[PDB]
Amino acid sequence: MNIFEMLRIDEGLRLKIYKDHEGYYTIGIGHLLTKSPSLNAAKSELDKAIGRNTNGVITKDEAEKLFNQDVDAAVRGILRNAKLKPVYDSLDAVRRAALINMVFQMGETGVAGFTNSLRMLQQKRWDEAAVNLAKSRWYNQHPNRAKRVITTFRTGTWDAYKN
Ligand SMILES: [Cl-]
Ligand SMILES: [Cl-]
Ligand SMILES: [Zn+2]
Image 1 (cartoon, rainbow, N blue to C red):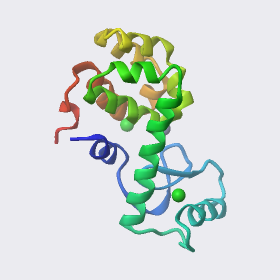
Image 2: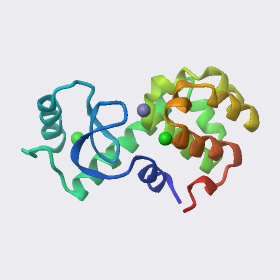
Image 3: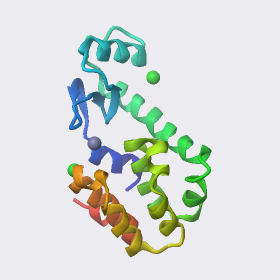
Image 4: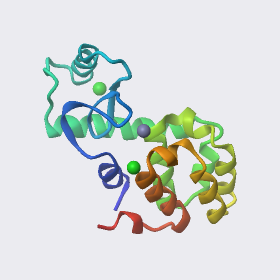
């Protein structure tokens, strides 16, 4: 398993613009288009992102392209951040993936705000981190997804994702 497969399971794949669980316009593999309520604004953004008049629909390949770009950006977000990098650098491969997943979902800034959990993870206090991470809006709004990520941080294995 790897980050891509992991995120593909958590985000799914949709080829037509859709409203996500937060009520925003998204497409492909969790690719947010706009937090605005206008579909037009979302189509504009889509065309801009893809480089063609899409009419709100894209191909698998195009979705995969947005996805590669998005995963790249999450990583770069991590590496650039003073609070995230040192943690990331302390972790094993599986756990790094769980950090990336969160950054992809919520943004570098968002994750950087989990001071306490970050600190526990850096100290390798897994069980503690996992409890702390669950005390969040993130967990409460996405219990199944959040449980898969937290487990991954807890065990360092891909178990939550096997299926
Ligand atoms: Cl793009
Ligand atoms: Cl969920
Ligand atoms: Zn959400």
